[PDB]
Image (cartoon, coloured by chain):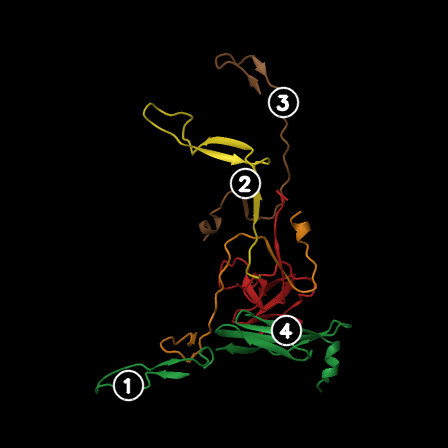
Chain colours: A orange, B brown, C yellow, D red, E green
Amino acid sequence: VWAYSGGDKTKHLFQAASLQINVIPDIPIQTTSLLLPLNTPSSFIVNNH
Amino acid sequence: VWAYSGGDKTKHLFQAASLQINVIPDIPIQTTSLLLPLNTPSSFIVNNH
Amino acid sequence: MDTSKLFKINSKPFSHLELLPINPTSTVIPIGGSMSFAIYLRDDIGEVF
Amino acid sequence: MDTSKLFKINSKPFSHLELLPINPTSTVIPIGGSMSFAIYLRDDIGEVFTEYGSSAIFSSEVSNTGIISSSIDANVVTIKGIRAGLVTLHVYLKDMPH
Amino acid sequence: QQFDSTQYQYMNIIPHIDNPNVLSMTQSSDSQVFTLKGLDQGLVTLSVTIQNPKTSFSATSKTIQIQVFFRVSPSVLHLVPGGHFQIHWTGGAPIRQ
């Protein structure tokens, strides 16, 4: 990412050091999934009847 | 079911005794499923890569 | 395990057979023309192999 | 077992938070008009939490006061325009403010 | 004031990581100390939350980060006057440096 003025875009004021993003492979088998925080009740059984 | 002629449909020639069909409830959680005959290899792993 | 997936495999004999037309546009075939029909195999609850 | 189904349950802490607009028709809000934003919570691989529990209390701050007002209900922040101008809205998980 | 290590046995300690596949964690034979291990090349964000198991009250650290892991290429260059070139480089902290 580079920061410019809104009024001047011909030259950047600042540039960031680049962040890496590491993408993880999925397993292509459609599997009903929940993700819950710790110590927490889930209404899933009622919501899906 | 009732059998008629294709020319005469005003009265049935024959009627069957009624068949019952017993519908079973699903569990509405989308779950990747196979159904294989006995003693049989499956290509599923290659087909889904 | 957090990226993982789940699946079911049923093992059964064939219980029923169904011949059905592959996307027909009339109920009929002409002299010199042709239509294709798929064979479906099912278990004791209508699940397709 | 032949009619049965399978499912996964993950148990994790919240790792990331995202405030995103609910079907915006514009990048600008008119004076007296309003827009709503959903709060998403994610794990360490970007998977979205299916239910947040009763501990997921949110807060919001507004860097230029009286340009807008905000109000939170469940995991949705709604805002209203009061004066023209620029503002940053900030939103955080109250009792884990990182 | 810090608490003494002998009081950490009363505390609910909960570590937090974004990328456990690059940097793994275990707790040690002391409740106050954890052992980290690098598994593959990358960068990971880390924090810890402590909670009281009588009052449910908690506090959290700053977020910190750890990288899992500099030389120049070539070490010798030959040019003619009016020549142009770029210097290339390997290893270190390429996401932070």
Q: Earlier in the sequence, mark 1 or mark 4?
A: 4
Q: Are marks 1 and 4 on the same chain?
A: yes
Which of the two discs, 2 and 3, sits closer to the camera? 2
State the SS at label 4: strand
Badge 2 vs badge 3, beta-carbon distance below 8 Å: no
- The Cα atoms of the two marked residues, 2 and 3, are separated by 33 Å
Which of the two discs, 1 and 3, sits closer to the camera? 1
Which residue is denoted by mark 3 in the rendering?
B18
State the SS at label 3: loop
State the SS at label 2: loop
> How busy is the neighbourhood of tag 1: few (under 14 within 10 Å), some, or many (20 plus)?
few
Amino acid beneath label 3? Ser
Q: What residue occupies the far right of the structure in this picture?
A: E54
Label 1 lies in what chain? E
Which residue is denoted by mark 2 in the rendering?
B38
Q: Position of residue E16 (x, y in %)?
A: 61, 72
Quadrant in the picture for residue C45: top right
Label 2 lies in what chain? B
Amino acid beneath label 1? Leu
Badge 2 vs badge 4, beta-carbon distance below 8 Å: no
The residue lying toward the viewer, choosing from A44 and A5, is A44
Up the image or down, B28 lies above or below C30; here it is below
Left or right of A12: which side holds D51?
right
Amino acid beneath label 2? Leu
Up the image or down, E82 lies above or below D33; here it is below
Badge 1 vs badge 2, beta-carbon distance below 8 Å: no
Which residue is denoted by mark 1 in the rendering?
E77
Which residue is denoted by mark 4 in the rendering?
E15
